Image (tube, coloured by chain):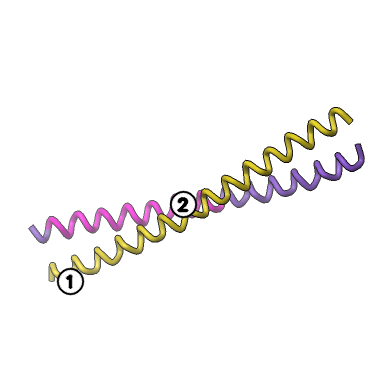
Chain colours: A purple, B yellow
Amino acid sequence: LKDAQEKLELAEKKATDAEADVASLNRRIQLVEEELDRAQERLATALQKLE
Amino acid sequence: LKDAQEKLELAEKKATDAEADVASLNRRIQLVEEELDRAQERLATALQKLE
């Protein structure tokens, strides 16, 4: 049980770290997605101006 | 020991799944950043042609 508890602590710390990484990376994903959406809207407007 | 090992198993599974999610989100970040860069380049070229 002692070794199992120590491994539990290590695993939960690592999982929490990876969950924070998930939160940060998903925030980056959404922000870059919004920037890409703005870029493609600008591209559509540019093609309209070309026409 | 049964409870301790069950907790170990659940924590390890959660940490492994979180690591996989982190890797997937990071590769998603790089993919979306590449797409964003291409969109920005297209925007610049289109604006120049428009002018």
How would you rate the neighbour count of disc 2 (Cα within 10 Å): few for under 14, some for 14-19, many for 20 or more? some
Mark 2 or 1: the one toward you: 2
Q: Is residue B50 left or right of residue B8?
A: left
- Mark found first going from the N terminus, 2 or 1: 2
Query: Dot 2 falls on which chain?
Result: B
Taking A17 as reference, is B6 above or below it? Answer: above
Q: Residue at x 35, y 58 (%)?
A: B35
Work out how far the residue at label 2 is from the one at label 1, CA to CA, in angstroms: 31 Å
Q: Is residue A14 left or right of residue A26?
A: right
Query: Dot 1 falls on which chain?
Result: B
Is residue B19 one of those drawn in magenta?
A: no
User: Split into 4 quadrants, where in the image is the N terminus of chain B?
Assistant: top right
Q: Position of residue B8 (x, y in %)?
A: 79, 37
Snapshot quadrant of residue A42: bottom left
Q: Secondary structure at mark 1?
A: helix
The residue indicated by pointer 2 is B28
How would you rate the neighbour count of disc 1 (Cα within 10 Å): few for under 14, some for 14-19, many for 20 or more? few
Residues in magenta, as a range: A24-48
Q: Residue at x 85, y 33 (%)?
A: B4
Taking A16 as reference, is B6 above or below it? Answer: above
Q: Position of residue B18 (x, y in %)?
A: 62, 44
Q: Residue furthest left?
A: A51
Number of numbered discs: 2
Snapshot quadrant of residue A44: bottom left
The residue indicated by pointer 1 is B48
Q: Are marks 2 and 1 on the same chain?
A: yes
Residue type for callout 1: Gln
Residue type for callout 2: Arg
Snapshot quadrant of residue A40: bottom left
